[PDB]
Amino acid sequence: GFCWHHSCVPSGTCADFPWPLGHQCFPD
C-alpha cells in the first residue's frame, strides 16, 4: 500500500500517479 494526496491506496493497488511517481504498484 501507499499513502498519497492525504489518501491511501491499499496493498495490491496500481495506479498512474504524476511524475516522478508514474505507474506504481503497492504490495504494502
Image (cartoon, rainbow, N blue to C red):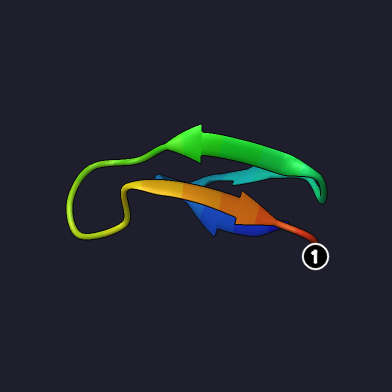
Left or right: where 17 falls relative to 14? left
Residue visible at 23% across and 42% down in the picture: 18
Relative to 20, residue 22 above or below: above
Residue visible at 20% across and 60% down in the picture: 20
Q: Where residue 16 sits in the image (x, y, percent)?
A: 40, 34
Left or right: where 25 falls relative to 19? right
> Where the C terminus falls, by quadrant?
bottom right
Q: Estimate how packed mark 1 is, as few (under 14), some (14 to 19) or many (20 or more) residues with alpha carbons within 10 Å.
A: few
Relative to 14, residue 25 above or below: below
Question: What amino acid does circle 1 point to?
Answer: Asp
Q: Where residue 25 sits in the image (x, y, percent)?
A: 62, 51
Closer to the camera in the image, 21 or 4: 21
- Secondary structure, mark 1, is loop
Relative to 8, residue 3 above or below: below
Q: Which residue is mark 1?
A: 28
> Where the N terminus falls, by quadrant?
bottom right
Q: Where residue 14 sits in the image (x, y, percent)?
A: 61, 39
